[PDB]
Length: 129
Picture 1: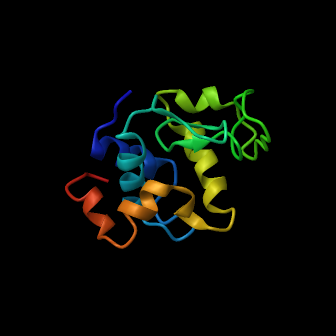
Picture 2: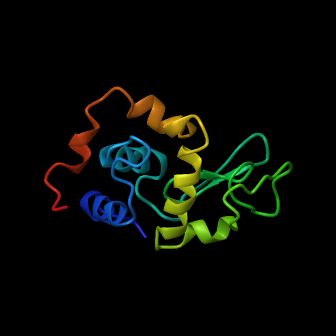
Picture 3: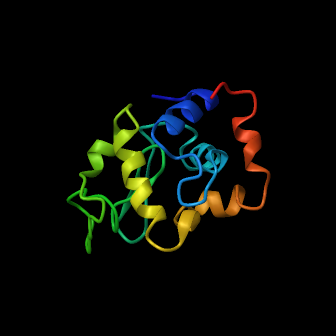
């Protein structure tokens, strides 16, 4: 599925991401835009043999198990295939674990390069929440 901007904002709000661990909702919408272009099926392969899955590009070395990544830790205790669903619930629940791990949203390269430091509340402007 490809989400619209406000559609995703609303879905993320219903799953408790607004101000979660100190990050307002606009951070999460911005991260999803530049990580996956709002596409739940985005995947990206890495030089360490890991793959990033889904709308928040969750990595298979640390967080989900894809059965092909050496050194997998599976800290979200979830198969990576579940993160390619059109329903964002599994991705959100894993994202909540990632941000609680101890470096916040810095786990998302596209967020720290392209969202951090800008007025991210513009990403939820004009949405009914």
